[PDB]
Image 1 (cartoon, rainbow, N blue to C red):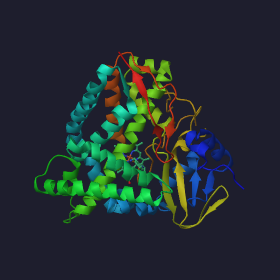
Image 2: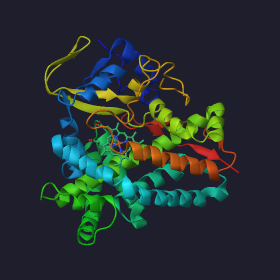
Image 3: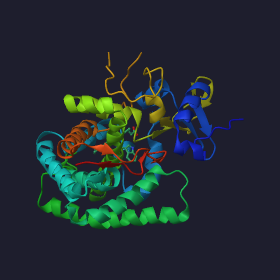
Image 4: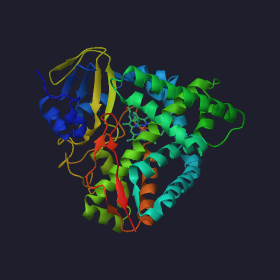
Length: 392
Ligand code: HEM
Ligand SMILES: NCc1c[nH]c2ccccc12
């Protein structure tokens, strides 16, 4: 019946031809392996994400507590979701952001100083993976002495959230990582409950729902939520950013001449190489897109990368171009989602990524690409295996 499958080996190598096929010939495409429909068009993805009543977040909550231990932001709605989401945003805004940024500069320069004498650096494996988890740890308030293990346990935890058909051995490891993470963080939450600091964990401890505070296991669940949410996409976007710029020397030069263009470059990178590729939702009642019928309980998976390359939303969608003027040839990209559950860390991510990119451009002179062709891996979250640059 249908022979093009998201789970073909060719898809993870290069999904762009699949994007083009699905939008034209099967915009709501059923995959029997996971009993879910994949949605490829910008307009349908946007409709799904903007109608939380019809397409809810019960899918995410399921295979998540096994590793989260309690309820995460996605499983919340109404005034609870708004209030707790505002609490988390408090940890990356106001005075917390003023204090956090100089620390992230320190993290960045410490990594640069570690590699500068070698005259090359892997933006993925030398910088991205290390900075991403340390930034998240600074945001939360976890001291960096054990960032090595924190990263290890995060990866096993993320693998569970971002995988579809994990075997019994893989499931048990991800669960062990979740327990090790919980063993490390509970004492920390106990300490900060006694002596508060200026970090996200302390914020969660001080939050007040009338006169009831978030229990210690829900603070950990939300802490793990933030650790996972903030770490994974940073590595990939940084690597994609410098790759696309170096693959387009002209645009790389424009960013050097007008450093203000770096924000536009990050946004175009998030559209072009969307690091979060899939957003699942659960259908709450009968519904039809084109002539594909959905039933209550069905699962739809928004294809963020496909939607951001939809020719109905962007002209020349498959070309990297930082000069895209929003003034249909341009639309707001879906890299941070949209609607009720849009990424709480969107503004922070843009600020943090611009900080890092500017510093890399300032300290690394005459950057030259060494990884002339990247190999990308992952279908749920996606990024290059390696992205090496050389410099003076
Ligand atoms: C380039 C970096 C990032 C990208 C591309 C990204 C992407 C996304 C996307 C697409 C969603 C929507 C998920 C859904 O609708 O089910 C989301 C949600 C979320 N993100 Fe991010 N994110 C990034 C960075 C961060 C950071 C730094 C944080 C720090 C806390 C964060 C925390 C969250 C949270 C808590 C949610 C859940 C929002 C809710 O349920 O209301 N993300 N993110
Ligand atoms: N906040 C980014 C984000 C959205 N969905 C995810 C799934 C796994 C890891 C990170 C993410």
